[PDB]
Amino acid sequence: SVIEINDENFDEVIKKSDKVVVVDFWAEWCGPCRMIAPIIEELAEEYAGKVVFGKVNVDENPEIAAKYGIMSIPTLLFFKNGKVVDQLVGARPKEALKERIKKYL
C-alpha cells in the first residue's frame, strides 16, 4: 500500500519508522512518472510490509520537494532513520529498483 505522504503525516511515516521508506515524487502532468507508478505499487506487494512505500505530489506539496532538493521528476528518495540515504533520478526497470533496495534491507 503506497501511502499518500503529505506535510501532516510526513514525520509520522518518515521519522518514526525503522524500515526503509521509498518515496516517489510525482505530478499528474508528468508522463515518465506514469512508468514508475505501477512498479512502485507492485514492489509494495512483493515486500510484505518489509519496506514502506510512499508518494509525494510535488504540486500539492511544492515545499517538501524544495527541502530535499528535487530538481526534476520522477525521482525516488530512500529514507532510513529520518535521513536520506539514496536518490534515484529518472524511471528505471523494476529489476534495477529491487537491486538498489536490497542494500538497505
Image (cartoon, helix red, strand yellow):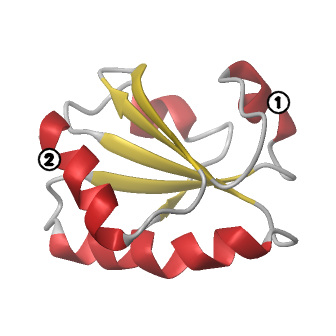
Secondary structure of the residue carrying tag 2 is: helix
| Precedes in sequence: disc 2 or disc 1 | 1
For the point 54% across and 70% down, the residue is: 36
Where 25 sits versus 81, above or below?
Answer: below
Q: Which residue is tagged 1? A: 63
Q: Which residue is tagged 2? A: 102
For the point 38% across and 31% down, the residue is: 79
Q: Position of residue 16 (x, y in %)?
A: 33, 28
Q: Position of residue 43 (x, y in %)?
A: 29, 70
> Mark 2 packing: few (<14 Cα in 10 Å), some, or many (20+)?
few
Q: Tell me, yes or no, whether the two marked residues, 2 and 1, touch with CB atoms within 8 Å.
A: no
Q: Quadrant of the N terminus?
A: bottom left
For the point 42% across and 76% down, the residue is: 39
Where 86 sits versus 20, above or below?
Answer: above
Say what amino acid the circle numbered 2 marks: Lys
Q: Quadrant of the C terminus?
A: top left
For the point 48% across and 55% down, the residue is: 54
> Mark 1 packing: few (<14 Cα in 10 Å), some, or many (20+)?
few
**Closer to the camera in the image, 52 or 84:** 84
Using residue 5 as the reference point, say whether residue 84 is left or right of it: left
Say what amino acid the circle numbered 1 marks: Glu
Location of residue 71 by image quarter? top right
**Closer to the camera in the image, 71 or 11:** 71
Which mark is drawn over residue 78? Answer: none
Location of residue 55 by image quarter? bottom right
Location of residue 12 by image quarter? top left
